[PDB]
Image 1 (cartoon, helix red, strand yellow):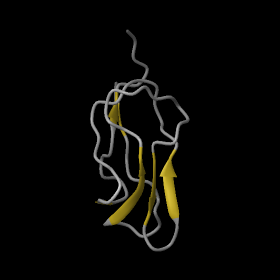
Image 2 (cartoon, rainbow, N blue to C red; image 1 turned 60 degrees about the horizontal axis):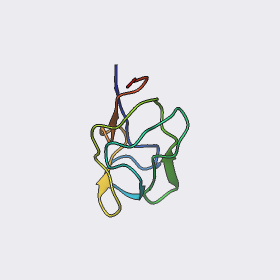
Image 3 (cartoon, rainbow, N blue to C red; image 1 turned 180 degrees about the vertical axis):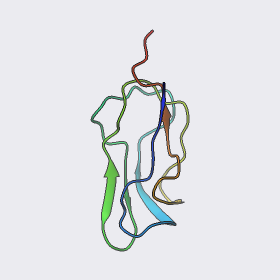
Length: 81
């Protein structure tokens, strides 16, 4: 159950400054919704979300560095109320 996002394919590898952040834990998410937009020194990546529930955690923003697969945001996925 639940899910844990992960840094996209910015191209480089680790220590990559994010470019977009739209998650504060609590917002709904579907199986197709841009979560963020990252970039390093080759290209600008992003994540179209991959779940269907609510976020619990959040490890990303605008100004910090990240690395491919570093646990960004966790969700409930296929959750009910």
